[PDB]
Structures are given as structure tokens and as C-alpha cells.
Amino acid sequence: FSEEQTAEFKEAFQLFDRTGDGKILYSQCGDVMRALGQNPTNAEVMKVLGNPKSDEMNLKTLKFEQFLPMMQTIAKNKDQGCFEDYVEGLRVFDKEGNGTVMGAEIRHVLVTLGEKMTEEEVEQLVAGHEDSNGCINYEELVRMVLSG
Amino acid sequence: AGKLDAHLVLEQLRCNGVLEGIRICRQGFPNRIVFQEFRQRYEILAANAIPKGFMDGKQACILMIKALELDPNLYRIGQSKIFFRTGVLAHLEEERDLKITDVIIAFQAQCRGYLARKAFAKRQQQLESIFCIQYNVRSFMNVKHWPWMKLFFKIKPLLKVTRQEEEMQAKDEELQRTKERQQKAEAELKELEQKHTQLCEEKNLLQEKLQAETELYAEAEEMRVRLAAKKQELEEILHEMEARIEEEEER
Amino acid sequence: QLCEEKNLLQEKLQAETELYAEAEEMRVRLAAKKQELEEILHEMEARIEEEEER
Amino acid sequence: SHKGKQGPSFSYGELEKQLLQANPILEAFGNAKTVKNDNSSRFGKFIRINFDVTGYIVGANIETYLLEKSRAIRQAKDERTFHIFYYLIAGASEQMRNDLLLEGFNNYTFLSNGHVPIPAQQDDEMFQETLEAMTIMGFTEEEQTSILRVVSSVLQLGNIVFKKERNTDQASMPDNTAAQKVCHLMGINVTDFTRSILTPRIKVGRDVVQKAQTKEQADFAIEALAKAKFERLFRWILTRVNKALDASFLGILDIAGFEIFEINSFEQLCINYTNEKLQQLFNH
Amino acid sequence: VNKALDASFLGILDIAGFEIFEINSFEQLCINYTNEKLQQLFNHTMFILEQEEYQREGIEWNFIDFGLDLQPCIELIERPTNPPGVLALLDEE
Amino acid sequence: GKFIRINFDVTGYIVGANIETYLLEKSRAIRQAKDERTFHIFYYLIAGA
Amino acid sequence: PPHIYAIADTAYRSMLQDREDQSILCTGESGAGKTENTKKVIQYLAVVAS
């Protein structure tokens, strides 16, 4: 990570403390990595956190110098999703080859499989992509979260 | 309950066909799947069993059966469909679900990502806007107690405003009346403020004096009030109890 | 409001001890009332039970 | 009527401007090369022009007829599909090229005789001409890009395959890419599409007769689907055109002419029917 | 009830169970009839049918007689013309 | 006997329900055997009334 | 583990999977519980599929 960005990373990390010690609760790590344009899965984050425990995940803290070493470790990975397959999976919920899925079925799956999201999480996501018939076009929603 | 007659339950299992009902599950192949759906669902298991070119559904899928080195006793190839043995298809399903787990889950991630970078870059907007808000308040807290600033304050209104208003003949008259009223109000307000200040001072003095007898009295009063409240509650409870008792007696 | 507070303070001064005494008296009265109520309730309950049996 | 004020040199009114650019549009999705005419009108047409009392043009309707959209799937020997197709496969911009998954010629199976050329006509430019027209007419900048993907779509849906299955005997979807793409352009979904396309979760009479068709049926549908998805377009544009072009009216009738090739299908029957019809009118 | 409760359907069947008291009236006859009926269904779909398809697809399989049939006991009460059934007679008679 | 039928849409949700009732032994509505009763509702009514 | 709620879900899915209506037939002699087990199947599907 060129100092150019590393220099800015700090600007982002710093831009993450409600009080002021200059520490990111073991929890925040995830969002801070994300904010830095990272899409680490929920596991990829714990793995580099020593797999703590809920309780201590709200007590433990972080300092950029000890955080940076993780930002990268993640940064360099083996895979990533992509329209190609990403949508290929949602298209399996397309009731009748319409090319669209019901914002309720999409809202389900997303909160009942794998890294289960929250009712609100999905709400905030799909919200505004459902049509008159509450129909979402994955192809697009895919790109949205993606290219976005 | 807890009683279980051996033979009575032995016959039932006899006239119902249970055993036989099980022999075929072990004997035959209760699971079958057509050549297409098979090379469809579990191809992901043998990505290189079937060549890049096309091929006959059957044969083309018999390839991937060798690719899993499936025992020739679990399955039974037919005309249009394959007949498997119990559990053989379950395991096949498991594997496939494993072969794709990571990927699943996959999307959810990018969502937390997207869903994140955005809602953070949001708190960012309320921020210079924050600062503005931040500092801005602080001013006031400091200022509001400053002579000069109070002055500006009472005065800030007289600004603009007249001569025309005064002239207006009707308007002018109205303005004059308003001014007079305002002056009166101001005087009244000042008087009230003075009175309030005096009262406050008196109250403070009284409080000090009370702090010891006064303090004790206050404490006593508080205690009395609490006691009264408790008593009232107790009375209410008692009444309720009495009513309940009466009802019970009647019943 | 200030005037009211002042008046209260004055009374207490004449005051905290006096207030405390009054409170104590009130509490005692309340307690007595509560006891009476409880007794009445008990009696009522007994009567009700008897009635039910009958 | 004029805003006051050499060959084609002349500034026409505002509507007459469009009235002029209409026919060059329907000519795209509607005309195609045949053993009788490089740019044949593949559908009867009856244009109606409306005049006020002063004698000025004020409106214009267009009643389209028998659109032989059959050929949208399979073209006879030395014949072509609806111009627009070729126009697109070529006039497509590099960017938008992929945007609709517009592989080159002969990468699509709905184009029999691969890519056949038209004498004195350059499809390359032909695109812009019609593109240009569409704008003159009124189709929003994007309002067009769309009408184009829906075209590629009507072509991809042709790649989709269904190879028999000697095991079950219900051909399947051995390849995703095909419908994979297609379902994207449709704003719909794969899996669903697939099932629906292979296993019709139908509902006959008082029953949810869930069944699965045979390789063939698997196509007769994916085929007669795109084929009708097309017509759904023509009829659409036509009402988009007719939306701008709109006491007296002048009627101009351009029916399709007596045509009689090798395979004298149904189309040719109603066509040579009307032709016989009209003539009799003149006789009467 | 059915006025409020009203592509796919799930079917749940609660028939009355083989019952046999003192007075074995008509009711008990159709009841223990259905019971005999249903069972045979399980026998068909369980042994009969299953083996037919093994044949059809033509897989390496030999038949197996589980000896489970009650068709007979049904004819004795179901069948009409030809050897009449218990129900038959009681109908015309 | 009773055969309940539940109806689902394409998304997999319950939407309807039918009920095919059969051999209602209403005989017993007039005379019940030894140590047996009539249709619950009867007693319910004679009491819950 | 084997439980009625299981037979109910196994069917209710099987239906939505291979698209082909299903039946849950409770046999057993009188008293054996033909009914109860039905009330459950509805009980389950009333929440799991509603």
C-alpha cells in the first residue's frame, strides 16, 4: 500500500472514533475495511481478529499501526464474486424466467442463507428497486451493489 | 400411556406391511433421476469428465459417474433415467452444496460492503455540516452571557425602519401606539425580572437558614409524603382484596 | 414559582423539623388506615368464602 | 403549413418533418431482402393523413397489418431477416456492442444464410440513418438503446439449446451462457425462465397440471417466444410513431404484393388473398 | 367453513380407522371397507408400481413377490356386475 | 373421514383450502351405544348454553 | 430426528422442487392417532409456508 494511500488510510481510520483514544473497537474493523473499498466476508474478518467473542468484540480496540497490517492481509485474496456467477445464483429464484424476482423472495434468501443479513439491512438495500408489483431486476441490483 | 402390548403392536406391523415396506428400500433403488437433471445438478462435481463438445445425455453423464468412481451397486442406469440407492443422492447433494457454499454468502458480503461504504460516507455529510453546527453552538453559550451581546439583542429589533411609518397617517398612529405598548411591556418585564431576582435571593437565604432545622423539616415533609402515598396504595390494595374475598365467598 | 418555593421554604424553616413532624404524623395515620383496610379485607374474604361454601 | 419563409432542399413544417421520418423507421423492423426484392415491405400498410378546413396537414395515422414475423427465426434461401437485425449487428457501437451482447454475424442461429449483403445498400450506415430517424421521430435517447437490446435478445434466444435426453427423454439446458444472457436482457430470471422453459408449471382446466415438454417443445416455445416477442416490438414502435404523427383525410394504401415463392405458407395465403381482394375492389 | 378457507396442493387424509365394536352395522362396513381400500393403495404404490418402472426403464432387476394384496376382499364388497359385491346385492335387493 | 386440501401459489405460499368430508355416522345422533356419546356439540350445548 | 413436522416439510418442499402435488396419508387402526398427526401437519404448514 503506497504511502500515498497509507497516508489516507489513516484519514479513514481516524474518521471512525466516537470518543477519541484513536481506537477502533474490534467490531468496527469490518466497516473500516469496507469503507476503504474492501469487501471482506464475515469470516475473512474474524480470521484476522483471532476469532474473538461477541463480548470481547465490543471491548477490544485497535490502533492504525496494528490495523494496517490487517487491511493488506485482506486486500490480497484468492477470489471474489462477479456478475457472471453472482446473478447466476439469484436467477434461480426467478419464478418464471421473467428476469425479475419478488422483492420479498429476494428479501428472504438474503436473510436466511449463509452470512444471514438483517431485516433492516436488506430493506435498505433492495428498497427502491421493487416496481409496482414489488419486482426487482437482479441483473441490475447485482450491478448496483457491485459497480457501486 | 406407557403401556405397550408386544403382540398387538406386532400384528399391526404385520397387516400394515412395514417390513416389506422396508425390504424394497434396502433391496431396490427408491431414487431415480433423469439423465438431464443429473448431468445438470452434479456437473460441478466433475468439471472435466464431459468433454467441451456435446454428447448423448446418457453416455455423457455416465462419464461423470466414473468421475465420481461411484460404486456399481449404488446406482442402476436405465433408459432415460438413473436409479440410485438410498442415500447415494443425498451425499451427492451435500458435496455440491459445499462446492458452492463460499460463493453463496459471497454476494451477502459485497452487500455489507456496498451497504457500508455508503452509510459511512453519509455521517460524513452531517460532519463539515457538523463543525458548522459544532462551533456555532459553542459561540452562543459564551456570548449569551456578554453585556454587549445582550445589548445587541434587545437592540437588534429597532433596526431595519421608520419616518414613513410615523407619518402614516393611520400607519404612523398605529406605529406610535405600538411603540408605547412595547415600552410599557419592556418596563413591566424589567420590573418582573427585578422581582424574580429578589425572590430568588430570598429563597436562597431561606434554604440556607433551613439547612439545619429547615433541612430537617424538608426531609420530614418528603418522608411524610412518601408515607402518605404508601398508605394510599395499601388502602387501595386492601379494598381490592376485600372485594375479591367477597366475590370468592359468594362463589 | 419562586414565590411558592419561598413560601414552602419558610414553612419548613418555621421549618424542616416541622415538615418532618407533619410527614411522620401523616405516615402514622396512613399506616393505621392501611391496617384497618387490611383487617376489613380479611373479614370480607372470610365472609365470601363462607358464602361460597353455603 | 409553413413557419413563414433544389431537389430535397426545403425546410418543412415541424410535424411534416416527422411525417417524413416515419416510413424510414417502420422500414427497419418490417422490411427485408427477398428473392423478389432487396427491400421488401413485409407487411401491408395503410397511412392516413388528416387535413383541416383551410387545407393543411395536421395529423397522420398508420394501420399496419400482416407482419410476417415468422422469418424472424428462419429465413429462406438467399433471403434475410428484418433489416434492423443486420443494421444492429453492424451499426452497433463498440461500447453498446457488448451492452446487448452483440456477438458478430454467424454467431446467431436466427440468421439463415449467415450474413447476406444487400446491393447498393450499406447496413453500416443504414444504422445511423434509422438511428437518426428514430430521433427525428421522437424516441428518447435511451428510449432507443432499449429497443435495440430487445433486438439482440430476440436473437440470443436463438442460441439457447435443448439436446434430447435418452435417459429421461426431456432435453435439457446443458449450457447456461445462452439463456444466461437472454434472461438478463429481459430483466427477468434464469432458473425461473429455465424451469418454465423446460418444465411448464402450467395449470390446465381445474388442475395445476405440472409437466415437462420434449426437446422439440422446449424450442417450439423458446422459438415462438422470441418470434412473438418481436411482433410485440413492431406494434409498439408503430404506436410510438403514431403517437407523434397524431374534417378530411387522404388515404394511401401499401399492401404487400402478390408473392409466390417455393414454400407457399399461410402468410402467402392471406397476402395473395388481400391482393385478390383489393383487385376485385377495382373491378367493382 | 370451506367458504373462507377458499398451481399446487398438499393433500392430508384423515379417514376413520378400522373400528369393530359389538354391533357391526353398515357404517362399520364401509368404514372398514375404506380402511382395507387405502391399505391396498400403499401395497400398490409400494411394491407393485415400483417394480413396474424398474421393468419399464429396463434396469437389471428381477421381481419380488411381497405377497401383499387385498383386491379380493374388495371385490367381495366392491365389484358390481359379475360376481356381485356385498354392497351390490344390498342395493338391488 | 376427512381429506383436507391446501393450495399454494408459485412463490410457495398458502392461499387456499378445501375439505372433502365423507361417511358421517349421523346414525348415533338418535341412539348411542353403551358407554358412548353423541356428537360433542350436543353436550356442549346442553351445558355451555 | 424423525418427527411429524419433518414429513410435513419434506413434502411441502418436494412439491415446490419437482413441481408435483403431494399427499400425506395417515393410516393405522382406530385410535392410533390418525387425526392429531394431521392437525400438526397443518399447524406446521400454517407458519412455515404462510
Image: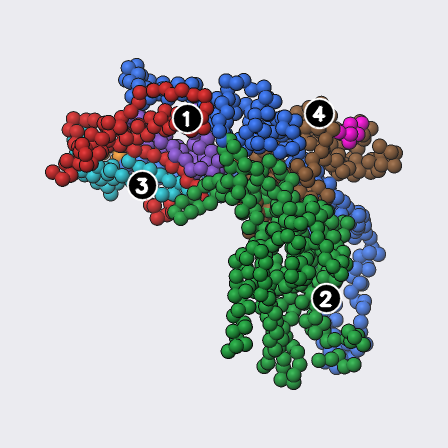
Chain colours: A brown, B blue, C orange, D green, E red, F cyan, G purple
Q: Crowdedness of circle 3 by 10 Å Cα count: few (<14), some, many (20+)?
A: few
Please tell me which residue is depicted at 69% across the width and 73% down the height of the picture: D15
Chain at tag 1: E
Q: Quadrant of the N terminus of chain B?
A: top left
Same subunit: marks 4 and 3: no
- Type of amino acid under label 1: Gln
Q: Which mark is residue D136?
A: 2
Q: Quadrant of residue D265?
A: bottom right
Q: Circle 2: is it few (<14), some (14-19), or many (20+) Cα within 10 Å? A: some
* Residue A29 on image: x %, y %: 73, 32
Numbered label attached to residue F20: 3
Which chain does the numbered disc 2 sit on?
A: D
Q: Does residue B208 appear to the left or right of A76 in the view shown?
A: left
Asked which secondary structure carries label 1, the reply is helix
List the single residue furthest toward the left.
E93
Query: Can I make out residue B196 in this image?
Result: no
Q: How far apart in space, not on screen, are marks 3 and 1 (Cα)?
A: 36 Å
Residue F33 place in picture, x, y as percent: 16, 31
Could you confirm whether marks 2 and 1 are on the same chain? no
Is the residue at mark 2 from the same chain as the one at mark 3? no
Judged from the image, the secondary structure of the residue bearing numbered disc 2 is helix
